[PDB]
Length: 201
Ligand SMILES: Nc1ncnc2c1ncn2[C@@H]1O[C@H](COP(=O)(O)OP(=O)(O)OP(=O)(O)O)[C@@H](O)[C@H]1O
Ligand SMILES: [Cl-]
Image 1 (tube, protein in one colour):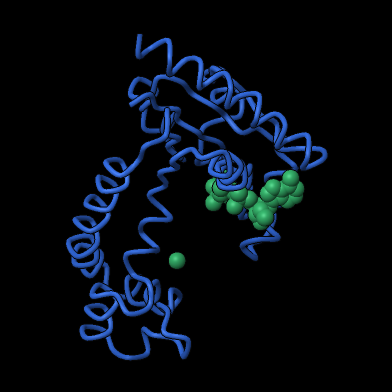
Image 2 (cartoon, rainbow, N blue to C red):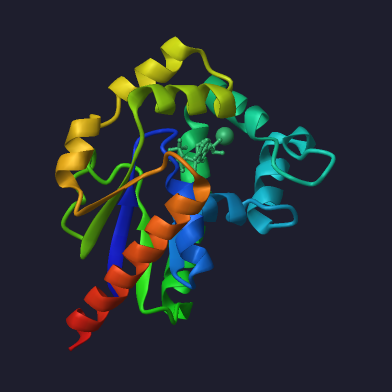
């Protein structure tokens, strides 16, 4: 299936832009979303986590207490392997199920480390969601409750803005009015529909 890889730095709005494509009927694959769904309330994986590490891993609303699980892995690095063994097969299975169930003309794959892990060859097209550096920092501080200095450290551990733009086939700036960003998505959607038809012929 024709595949567009969406990437961008922390705070740029990968998920925000992907949602607009989803609204146009595009199947969006995002490993972070899938990882959250495999540990949703009532899931067997969440039960396994609670039975190993304790009922305090479950909040009163039935969801995973993510901070308590991060604390457990921080104190016991060996439990990272256990968590990976539990969750990776479920994430792989659900990724494949979603691919198979899709009936849209193309797939949008959210790939946060596309450039860093050198995956710029798997997708038919690369879309970069871009914002100024200061915008990344401001949106990350707000969402994640980190210091500006912490946000800067994350940026330094990710691909540079220039590297991401160099790899992009198309760039969407997640700035200005939300309506215009959505119109930009609609224009790219038509481009991708036509490229998918061209590939199919
Ligand atoms: N146009 C915008 N103006 C202001 N804030 C925005 C805008 N678009 C998204 N945001 C906010 O910016 C933050 C980052 O957005 P989002 O979660 O889509 O980022 P991401 O690139 O998918 O994720 P990550 O930073 O984890 O890599 C969120 O709090 C989102 O609400
Ligand atoms: Cl977390």
